[PDB]
Each structure stands twice: as structure tokens, then as C-alpha cells.
Amino acid sequence: GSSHHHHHHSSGLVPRGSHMANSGEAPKNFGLDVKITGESENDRDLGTAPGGTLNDIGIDLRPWAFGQWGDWSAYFMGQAVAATDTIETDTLQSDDGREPDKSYLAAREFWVDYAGLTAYPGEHLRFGRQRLREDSGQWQDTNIEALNWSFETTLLNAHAGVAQRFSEYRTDLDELAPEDKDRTHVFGDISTQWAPHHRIGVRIHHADDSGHLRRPGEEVDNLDKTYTGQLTWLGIEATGDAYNYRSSMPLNYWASATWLTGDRDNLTTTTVRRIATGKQSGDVNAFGVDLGLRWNIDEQWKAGVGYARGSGGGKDGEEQFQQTGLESNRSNFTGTRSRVHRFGEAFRGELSNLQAATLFGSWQLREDYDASLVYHKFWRVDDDSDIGTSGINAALQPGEKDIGQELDLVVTKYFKYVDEPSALIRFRGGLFKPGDAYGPGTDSTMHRAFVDFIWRF
Ligand SMILES: CCCCCCC/C=C/CCCCCCCC(=O)OC[C@@H](O)CO
Ligand SMILES: CCCCCCC/C=C/CCCCCCCC(=O)OC[C@@H](O)CO
Ligand SMILES: CCCCCCC/C=C/CCCCCCCC(=O)OC[C@@H](O)CO
Ligand SMILES: CCCCCCC/C=C/CCCCCCCC(=O)OC[C@@H](O)CO
Ligand SMILES: CCCCCCC/C=C/CCCCCCCC(=O)OC[C@@H](O)CO
Ligand SMILES: CCCCCCC/C=C/CCCCCCCC(=O)OC[C@@H](O)CO
Ligand SMILES: CCCCCCC/C=C/CCCCCCCC(=O)OC[C@H](O)CO
Ligand SMILES: CCCCCCC/C=C/CCCCCCCC(=O)OC[C@H](O)CO
Ligand SMILES: CCCCCCC/C=C/CCCCCCCC(=O)OC[C@H](O)CO
Ligand SMILES: CCCCCCC/C=C\CCCCCCCC(=O)OC[C@@H](O)CO
Ligand SMILES: CCCCCCCCOCCOCCOCCOCCO
Ligand code: NA
Ligand code: NA
Image (tube, rainbow, N blue to C red; front, side, top):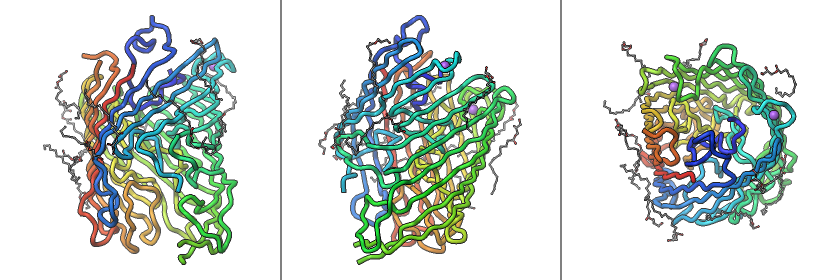
């Protein structure tokens, strides 16, 4: 169930001989996830800089161990990567001493779990570096050091947790991303199934920076904070099988509305090299919405439409929405077993001063195949402000809303007619056509494409 150490993994695979594959089998005490990935990426900077391209292959080995003693359990997953260049073998990885190596080791998850606070097996308390995820992937979908309480039953779901990054636990990164340094997260949610397959809930997330900004006159570099914040997100979300590839309803939907409030102290800088010149404080009062509708046309075919908007601009930036920093924006919103980046495998938009229209169609055959075709159109909301994170590394021209368009294709075979697959092979690709906001001299297209072979043993 929810408690299982691989429950949140997008792969959805089940090792042969595991208790999930056959309930007569004992829970596995160990296993191995093998991933072989090729990545083609050109051009992340749209041709406005040297390099920024990938055509490379890697292997990622993830051994894991699991022990259970009554109400106590413990879990470790490690990671060993070897690649021909620094490709993305891990969809949950984000961002001098932050250059990844072509090969590295990592401690991916390490936690202890206690399920005895209540008699519900859906209720448990987990402590350590662990997978945090909610179904939208837009609040949390990451491996992070946390103390997280989960309560998942038929009629009531609730979670409450605290998290903070202290290390990457990687042989090649020595330092945290500035955004993560000294940032503490506190969060909770409560939701109820008010009708079969219809959920309504509220969600809260609070991020608190205890860091300091560089002082005036000090040089600022890659690894320094751009800002410190006290930010609270308060959201309501309604879903009808929003992310359930096995829905029997003719229509699935999601609707979320999120208010961001709090305050930011922003570092100001000038060039001389970058030098700090001061800081400016201000309140944040921003808003995000994500809406979608999926038609379940028959047993195999689905289609849908999406609309998202993160506010931008406003009186000294108060209306600039942003996400928690723990999000993936990866979800099953196209109604298949395969998770898809909600704002493009190529653009990888953060919902920050961003408006997106989305169309998709998908096809699924039992547990054996799925395919998604996704079209996105992106606009800035305030054309004098930047957007948030994105997989495109090029500057936006002031006064231009048209960010661009994207076409994504995901195609997956699961295997090892198959009841519960234990392996998959997947093509994951996005084609991004930059709009006028990227100005002249840009590449007319860029792409990011992956082939992933995943095996769970
Ligand atoms: C299904 C029909 C359509 C086909 C889809 C395939 C999509 C390709 C996506 C990923 C391609 C990865 C290319 C790997 C190059 C590896 C290499 O040996 O070069 C290393 C050298 O560059 C040193 O750095
Ligand atoms: C704060 C973060 C804490 C990090 C803890 C990391 C723990 C590492 C996982 C190792 C799993 C525990 C070791 C297994 C014990 C020997 C055994 O086999 O016990 C029987 C078992 O097979 C029953 O299921
Ligand atoms: C059933 C067939 C499935 C198809 C996949 C089988 C292929 C398995 C091998 C994958 C290994 C790729 C990573 C090699 C690391 C090389 C390296 O460390 O790079 C050094 C230097 O050359 C880079 O600059
Ligand atoms: C079946 C074959 C599988 C083979 C792969 C086994 C999986 C890997 C085990 C995981 C080992 C992770 C240890 C992380 C240490 C981080 C660190 O020391 O960082 C130092 C650096 O930051 C400088 O300060
Ligand atoms: C905003 C985020 C805050 C969320 C964290 C909440 C922690 C506080 C606990 C408070 C306990 C109240 C429990 C109500 C009774 C439960 C019940 O009805 O029984 C389960 C049954 O319905 C299933 O079979
Ligand atoms: C990038 C591609 C984006 C495409 C996005 C499209 C979004 C909307 C999907 C709308 C699907 C509704 C189809 C109507 C069902 C056909 C029907 O009813 O035939 C009669 C049958 O019901 C009697 O048996
Ligand atoms: C390491 C080489 C690279 C190091 C980068 C620099 C700093 C290293 C500090 C390492 C401190 C690690 C503490 C483990 C805590 C896990 C846990 O128990 O969870 C905490 C709780 O859940 C939080 O809320
Ligand atoms: C520029 C703004 C453009 C806005 C257009 C957005 C287009 C995207 C489709 C979103 C369709 C909304 C679906 C969620 C509402 C579900 C619902 O109300 O049902 C009640 C429930 O099912 C009772 O059971
Ligand atoms: C038939 C055989 C199957 C072949 C597969 C073909 C897949 C085609 C996907 C292409 C989907 C692109 C949709 C463009 C949206 C229209 C639009 O809005 O552009 C105007 C602009 O947004 C502002 O007005
Ligand atoms: C290199 C990237 C590799 C990505 C692999 C994706 C799979 C290739 C496209 C397969 C999708 C084609 C759809 C027709 C086959 C489904 C069907 O109607 O027949 C089912 C029958 O075969 C049951 O077994
Ligand atoms: C390296 C520069 C030249 C790039 C050509 C190789 C690219 C290989 O990957 C294919 C491109 O990515 C595909 C994006 O998905 C396309 C979606 O539209 C398909 C319509 O059915
Ligand atoms: Na419990
Ligand atoms: Na569906």
C-alpha cells in the first residue's frame, strides 16, 4: 500500500517474486533497480552560448535494502551512476562545487519508519532521507531528509511533515543549491473522499530561510542565495481520478487554487563580476491555479485539456507566484501509468509568472503499453518579469509574453499479457519551439529526448 518503499516511484514496477507480485511471497528484504538511459538534448541555451547539448548514455544502479520488525521498518537505497556525459538519469534531481561528475555514488534514501501510532496500516511516521510526493507533483516530489507523518484511509487522508536539506549525499556535489541551504519546510494536508473517486482537500506548505544574504560590497557567486523568504502556500484541490490510469469514470478532473503569502528579502547586485549592493524586502501575495479535464473515451483512449497560471509581476513583485522547490511537476495527468512533466519534458516550466494551455491524447493497453502526445502553449503573465525555473537556459526579452510552444511524446512498453510488469522501456521526448520572448538569434527549435530501460529485481 501507501507505506511501501517504492509506492511513489513513477516506474510502477513490481519485482518478480515480491510480495506485491504474489501476496504469498515474503516482503523482499532487498532488491536492485537498474536503469539505462540515453539522452539527446539540443540546445538548452537555444544556440545563444557554447555547448548546452547532450548525446550520451549512462547506467544507474540502485540497490536497496528493507527490514521490517512489527511496527518498525527501515530502508536504504543507494545509487551508482556511470555515464559518457552528465545526463539526467534521475527525474527528481534539480539544478563552483555544484558541477556533477559523469560518474558518482549517492545515498538516495535512508529512513526508519514507525507504524504503531495507530492500528491503520495506512498510518505511519517516517524519519530520514525519504521520498516525499503528492499526486500532482506540484508541491513535493523529491528525496529529502524529513520527519513525515502519513494517514491514508478510505475517507480521510492527512499528512504532516518537516523537511530540510543538509547534503546531497553525493560523491560529486560538495554544497547545496543556494535555494536549499538553511531552508526549512513544514507542510500538511487533509482531504476526504466525499464521493467514490472524488477527493477534496486543503494543503499547506511553509518555507523558512534562516540563511543570510551577502553583504553590500561582497562578491556574489553561483552558490550564494538570491533571496531569503518566509513563504506560506495555502491550497484547495479537488480531484476526480485526476491521476488514476485505471479510472472507470468517463471523465477525470483536477482543480487546484493556491495562495502564496509571506515575505521575501531580495538581494540586489551589480556588475564590476557580481557584487552585492543591498537588499529589498516586500510581501508576497500571489496565486496559482491548475485545472484539467480528461476524457476516458474508451478502455484504451483518453484525451484532455489543461490550464495553469502562476501569477507574476505586481507592485514590487508581490504577485510573483513560485513553487515550493520540492516539486517535480511530474504526474500521471494524461491518464497513463507513465508520469509526464506537466509543463513539458523540454520546457520543464515552474508555475511562476507563467500561463500554460495544454492539450493531450493518450493510449493505454492493459498494463503493457501506454503512449502520450502532449501539446503546450506558454505565455508570461507579466512581460517585464522573469519566469521561474525552466529547462531552457536563455534570457527573455522584456515586453514579450510569447514564451513558446511544445510537443511531447511519451511511449512505454512494460514487461517481464503481463500481470505486473517488472521492467519497462520508454521513449520520452519534447520539442520546444521558442516564441518571441526569446528574441532573435535563437534556435527555432530545441529538444530533450530520453530512452530509459528500467529493470526492477
Ligand atoms: C524509436 C525510434 C526513434 C528513436 C528514438 C531514439 C531517441 C534518442 C534519445 C537518446 C539517444 C541517446 C544517444 C546516445 C549516444 C551515446 C554515444 O555513444 O555517444 C557518446 C559520446 O557522445 C561521448 O560523449
Ligand atoms: C535516521 C535514518 C535511519 C537510516 C536507517 C537506514 C537503515 C538501512 C536499512 C537496513 C535494513 C535494516 C537492517 C536489516 C536487519 C537485519 C535483517 O535482515 O532484519 C530482518 C529483516 O530481514 C526483517 O524484514
Ligand atoms: C538489452 C540491451 C539494452 C540496451 C542498453 C545496453 C547497453 C548497456 C551499457 C550502458 C553503459 C553506458 C555508460 C558507459 C559509461 C562510460 C563512461 O564512463 O564514459 C567514459 C568516457 O567515454 C565518457 O566521456
Ligand atoms: C550491484 C552493483 C551496484 C554498485 C553500486 C552500489 C550503490 C552505491 C552505494 C551508495 C554509496 C553512497 C555513499 C555516499 C557518500 C557521499 C560522500 O562521501 O560525499 C563526499 C563528497 O561530497 C566530498 O565531500
Ligand atoms: C492541515 C494539515 C494538518 C494535518 C495533520 C493532522 C494531525 C492531527 C491529528 C488530529 C486527530 C483528529 C482525528 C479525527 C478522527 C479520525 C477518524 O475519523 O478516524 C479514521 C477513519 O475515518 C478511517 O477509517
Ligand atoms: C495533441 C492532441 C490533443 C487532443 C485533445 C482533445 C481534447 C478533447 C477530447 C474529446 C474527446 C471526446 C470524443 C467524443 C467521443 C466520441 C463519441 O462519443 O462517439 C460516439 C460514442 O460515444 C458512441 O458509442
Ligand atoms: C557529506 C558530504 C557532503 C556534505 C554537504 C555539506 C554538509 C553535510 C551535512 C550532513 C548532515 C547529515 C544529517 C543526516 C540527517 C538525516 C535525518 O535524520 O533527517 C533529518 C530531519 O528529518 C530533518 O528535518
Ligand atoms: C483562461 C482561463 C481558461 C479556463 C479554461 C480551462 C480549460 C481546462 C479544463 C478545466 C476544466 C475544469 C475541470 C474541473 C472542474 C470539475 C467540476 O467542476 O466537476 C464537479 C465534480 O465533478 C462533481 O462531481
Ligand atoms: C492524424 C494522424 C496522427 C498524426 C499525429 C499528429 C499529432 C499532431 C500534434 C499537433 C498539435 C498542435 C496543436 C496546435 C494548437 C492550435 C493553436 O492553438 O495554435 C494557435 C496558437 O496557439 C495561438 O492562437
Ligand atoms: C526505443 C524506445 C522504445 C519504446 C518502446 C515503446 C513500445 C513500442 C511502441 C509500441 C506501440 C505500438 C502500438 C501497437 C502495439 C499494441 C498492440 O496493438 O498490440 C499489443 C500486443 O503486442 C500485446 O503484446
Ligand atoms: C542533435 C541535433 C539534432 C537532433 C536530432 C536527433 C533527435 C532525436 O530525438 C528525437 C527528437 O525528439 C522528439 C520530440 O518528440 C516529438 C513529438 O512529436 C512527434 C509527433 O508524433
Ligand atoms: Na499505523
Ligand atoms: Na484516466
